[PDB]
Image: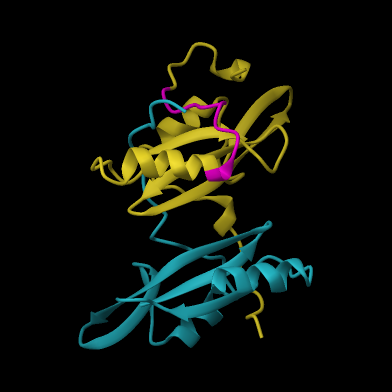
Chain colours: A cyan, B yellow
Amino acid sequence: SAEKLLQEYCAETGAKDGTFLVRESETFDYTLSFWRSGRVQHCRIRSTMENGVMKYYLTDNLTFNSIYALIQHYREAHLRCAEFELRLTDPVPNP
Amino acid sequence: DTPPTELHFGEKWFHKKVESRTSAEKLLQEYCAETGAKDGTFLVRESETFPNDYTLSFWRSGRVQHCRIRSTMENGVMKYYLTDNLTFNSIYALIQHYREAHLRCAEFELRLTDPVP
């Protein structure tokens, strides 16, 4: 899987954090995957209609006309992932 | 084995027994997958990668994220944090805070760099 492709390349390249690739969703959207401290992280890229025009985003308050524009922006500003920027809730009981 | 900064706090979510990232995800799946558990369901465990550090593992509809909780001494006082923007004197306080404010993990505090060829 793409998760593995990154694994290889990054581990076998000393690739710095931030090395990514964008893949098309499975049923819905695209998924962003990047190298970060030995692990491959990911975040869903969502889309919507903003006043009749198609947009993409990682977080609701900042949309883009395309995946290109979305990536380039997060190439100049640190990532934001609305998928995982949520509030903690219930604890898991026992180990 | 729980850190001294948590001695007087009730922490159902703290599991020093879960000694693996894989183990954490299974526990979360078993407990969350078909029980209707809310997103944000979590647990705290010792880091399997970084010494002295811990890891926050939570559930988000079929997904499990892991956020490193760094712990450093600052002027003779232990500080715990996800991002060095805000620190806490206990994991307890870090948890309660993120129960009222959206998470902001360090694994996302960076810019994308190069696309794999």
* Image point (74%, 70%), residue name: A15
Is B105 situated left or right of A91 in this image?
Answer: right
Q: Mainly helix, strand or loop, the magenta region? A: loop
Q: Can residue B112 be seen in this view?
A: no
Quarter of the image with the N terminus of chain B is top right
* Image point (41%, 87%), residue name: A66
Residue B43 to residue A12: above or below: above
Counting from the top left corner in percent of width and height, residue B35 is at 25, 40
Camera-side residue of A88 and A77: A88
Question: Total label count?
Answer: 0
* Image point (69%, 43%), residue name: B49
Is A95 situated left or right of B34 in this image?
Answer: right
* Image point (63%, 81%), residue name: B115
Q: Does the magenta stretch include residue B17?
A: yes
Counting from the top left corner in percent of width and height, residue B14 is at 49, 26
Is B87 situated left or right of B57 in this image?
Answer: right
Span of residues in magenta: B12-22
Counting from the top left corner in percent of width and height, residue A39 is at 63, 58
Please identify the quarter of the rendering in which residue A58 is found: bottom left
Counting from the top left corner in percent of width and height, residue B111 is at 61, 68
Is B2 situated left or right of A30 in this image?
Answer: right
Residue A86 to residue A23: above or below: above
Q: Is residue B24 visible?
A: yes
Q: Is residue A61 magenta?
A: no
Residue positioned most to the left: A52
